[PDB]
Image (tube, rainbow over all chains, first blue to last red; front, side, top):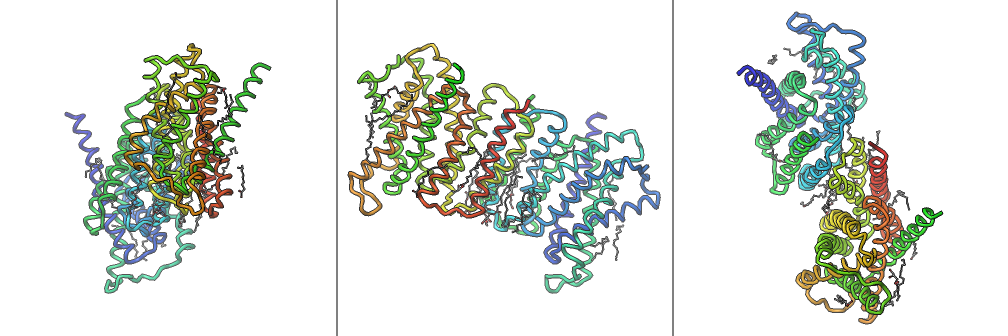
Length: 305
Length: 305
Ligand SMILES: CCCCCCCC/C=C\CCCCCCCC(=O)OC[C@H](O)CO
Ligand SMILES: CCCCCCCC/C=C\CCCCCCCC(=O)OC[C@H](O)CO
Ligand SMILES: CCCCCCCC/C=C\CCCCCCCC(=O)OC[C@H](O)CO
Ligand SMILES: CCCCCCCC/C=C\CCCCCCCC(=O)OC[C@H](O)CO
Ligand SMILES: CCCCCCCC/C=C\CCCCCCCC(=O)OC[C@H](O)CO
């Protein structure tokens, strides 16, 4: 029983990850529909999470990490990947329906398997190349039938696959290299990342968009409602990423990306219902084939030498 | 000297392959512009090749092969791959500019490497996945900017990659399994394939297109001139495929496809010149990136563990 029970506590971390991420995605897109500034918004979300974590340390509510220069340097690459994937994903969110963004990001386990095998010196069974046929065909079919498609919205989402895979693999190194450091719990690893990531993105956000006026492009929405939406999606942005690093602490980077693809099916279904996103038969079939292909690719990689 | 003598003779085979294939491609496209019946035209080209080979046998100009039940069974899958690839490629030739068809078929070495490794139990280095990025990006950019793009023209060309790789691999097995049958020279192997392939395609061709009237869609072409153009491209269709099996007999199936990609650079350059094909800046950048990626892919697979 304790073995299956331990998987229930870990599975609950995955549920929180999915539950917080769905609240984030809906509120984040509603913010972008009123306030189309992805650079500044994504930077705000990192800063709110940075401030939230420092408050927990100040109040003694969370163990303070024994920060060393060795750890900081070992967190640069996780932070560069997080910042780049975050800014690219928010840019995609601002340009297309978020359901299409998560379809593109559903190919993350393929990038994760390649990057992980490059590091671990592994090799791929030829059958994994066959499973790329439904993935490439599915994504191409989904993009060809997506009403909101733009080339920039598609490419920025594809970029985030590379950046987040880089984040997850390098973060996994740090978490294992500092396994005996009891103060570097999973939440503190992401806490330091979101603090570094904030200052990494901050100059780009100001150069790209400046200080956008706090005005809703949707007529009739007060500034207080716009500010509450910005703060609401920023709070749940941090919570879902924080809980996800608990999940990353308990699984491999590739398994983490598989858990992400399951998350995207939930977000895709939920977002098209909430937003009444128009979806044609070919578009549903294309997206479904691509995600089935990603699972088959993962199954082929896992079950073959 | 003996090994260099052989590689020089093999090199002359590749030259005849490229030279005959260029003559074919120009004449075949000029025929399709006048007489847009890809099923029947591709069937005629197989039959004219079948008749050419039987004349050599009847006149004593070429050793007759000892045809056995085992050999015919070993040539069914080579003929299936040849018929499907030939019919799919000709369909693509009739729908888009042949320069675009050969850009899509330039990815053949990737399919060939997967097919070989799948049969031989080989494994892929992770860096071969990175080389897919310029291949997929280049082909996508090329297709997004090709003025004559149609989905059917693109997909039929992609299908021929799978069919011809199947043909090359299964043919190489039969040629190796029958290496001690002295009557089965490389030209007799393809001679038997074009005979089987002709009768495989014939009922489908009549099913799809019936008996097309020998009338040119371009004014000023007599029926005799159209008939001459059909016979001309049919002769060089058989000649280039016949000499290519001399190349296949002396190289691996992967090296054969790499030779095919070199061939298509020549075909693409010559065809855009002869037909004055419109090519934008973004279009030949994408096509070049795609072919560079395929060559980088082949370099990675060959030079890596
Ligand atoms: C080994 C690496 C992978 C190699 C194998 C890659 C296979 C990709 C081939 C074709 C994708 C095209 C998918 C089918 C696209 C159909 C598009 C379509 O139906 O368009 C409808 C129209 O646009 C409605 O508006
Ligand atoms: C293994 C990792 C898998 C990830 C890689 C997936 C393969 C990428 C597929 C196609 C690239 C190009 C997208 C094709 C989209 C063509 C349709 C299109 O863009 O037309 C829209 C038009 O511009 C307005 O509606
Ligand atoms: C909720 C249960 C999650 C369990 C997960 C286990 C793995 C599921 C694998 C394949 C089914 C997923 C295919 C459905 C993908 C959504 C297709 C879709 O709705 O596309 C909308 C379109 O993309 C709008 O832009
Ligand atoms: C592990 C790696 C597995 C394989 C991963 C493959 C990822 C390639 C995905 C997308 C490239 C698409 C590039 C599309 C180039 C942009 C097209 C464009 O710029 O628009 C064209 C033109 O402007 C319209 O009129
Ligand atoms: C080994 C791997 C090599 C094969 C990898 C190939 C990847 C190509 C991806 C998608 C194909 C379609 C993408 C291009 C589609 C854009 C063109 C388009 O759809 O335009 C619609 C309109 O009908 C015309 O103008």
